[PDB]
Length: 46
Length: 54
Length: 370
Image 1: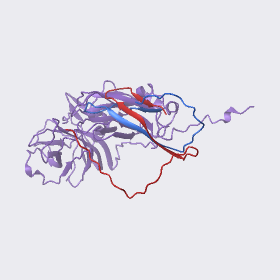
Image 2: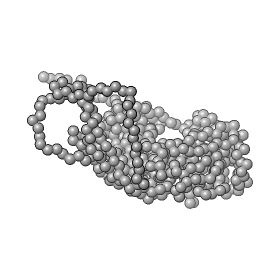
Image 3: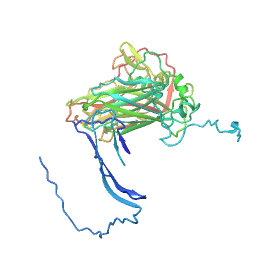
């Protein structure tokens, strides 16, 4: 997994929330192994 | 008030190169640009930790 | 199979060293309240009392089972805030502790101190030596000598945030060898490190003629309600009768960066009544930016004719005081959109070219700060 935790508290004067967007852009040194028969279904994002 | 965002398209001085994903012999760098998700940390929350499966 | 157990490397008496991941041993977070004032303490405890409570890191047991550590402790505090608010936090460390002590900024901020404003800095780090008279320390040494630590608030919120915050800090073992800092009585050096808290200066908004003064007769301590406050640097300075040298002050901004002012600092005498033709002295103009937080200004010893007394009786008049003063006056008005005040913190850090003259019999009493 990729875990993200707050080191300190979230400090602001407005009533908003702290939003981040993570994007896996590229995978260097890519090595693929095998052949996938497939698994039906996928997990929700966010 | 509601805003207006403008954009204008040009023809740059950059030649077109192809990006082809081969199945048999993939390269050493796989460009994905996969949207992993949005992380919303609230204010005044003590113990919060978000996880994204690889 | 039979090997000799006496030839194994189970006698490694080397200190802990490596990267910052392999040298962290403690991490403590403290709760900063939503509505705090100036002067209340956020944390005050011994270092051993918080270094062994639920802190299991990569260099925790290696620190707990090492007899001599030859590296200085590096501390990194991380707390950030937007520019429409502001406070001031001071982390001070001391060598020992007695019963029912005082939590003033003047008392605790003498040996090792890190004073910063989180609205202008993302994170602040500082390094200190737990053994001031030696080149090594240990965890049992900090347990037995009652090594104290305290985080205090010296200037409250200009504008209050939405909720109460949490400031975390983590202690490392830096790659800096421990050096001793010893104050000799007979032969003092050419640079006397004091870190004396001179006081807090609060300029209001819409005030036309305001000018603050700080006496340079800094010996004897600080005043309190039928009491005095002391530390070892002021007690060491108060042994001589007169002193002379060029002074190095540090000015910190303790308000929000949306409150702006231009302050002229100069050296004067007696009690003045804000004449506009007072900038004919050689004065320094201080004007803070948004990223600018702390400024060092040095008054050379060409501004001082002779030496002056370390201690002045507080029951004397203004005309009967011969010591020089440090005056700070507003060059222009105080401009902001919030309803806060413009706060400054002056600290005489060191006195270069130090010359002490005579021997002080002593004067009872001290003046109030601010």
